[PDB]
Length: 240
Ligand SMILES: [Zn+2]
Image (cartoon, rainbow, N blue to C red; front, top):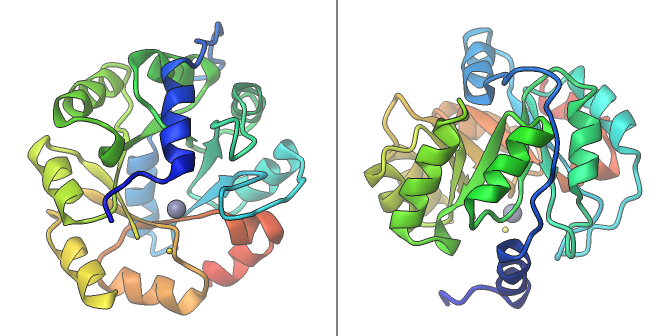
């Protein structure tokens, strides 16, 4: 069962050829992992709200990106903007328009395989990027992690199982996203992460009660997309 899905293998081909985007960012980096730590200090639930108009699982929402982002700036600890084009209907231009208008931290969520895609994130105004362990070698992951740090971005390193976590911990990731969409496995992964690493439960969250349960295990933030795209007001239920 360790095959990459058809759509992800196709995305990696699109990412390798992704043209770089010529631009200047309009404000400095605002740290997403530090703001998560500030929310935790204040005891307020930290949700990274994702913007995506489509997904390989069949999400299909037309929602204006500025209006979603304005509303989410009221509630969310940060935004995650999908910039993968074929399956999520994201775009660099949509990231640039959102990052020119909100002043909470922005994660560029895409499938990064080369340095120019981190240069594109910085030039478009994102504050950090997603790196996914399973599509990279360990040497590439360590190099891309250092490349993101060289701009002042602590990247979100996305892991799906214990082997991926083993790699993320070996290379000294400080910001890890735990994705699954089994209870003892999830508890075990969480429990392997050191106190100094900000941990994000990515996807597989539908109700407030799972957020509460994850918080007791020390999860620091929650990356949630589809449900918020279909009703942005759902984030009020989640932060209660
Ligand atoms: Zn997912």
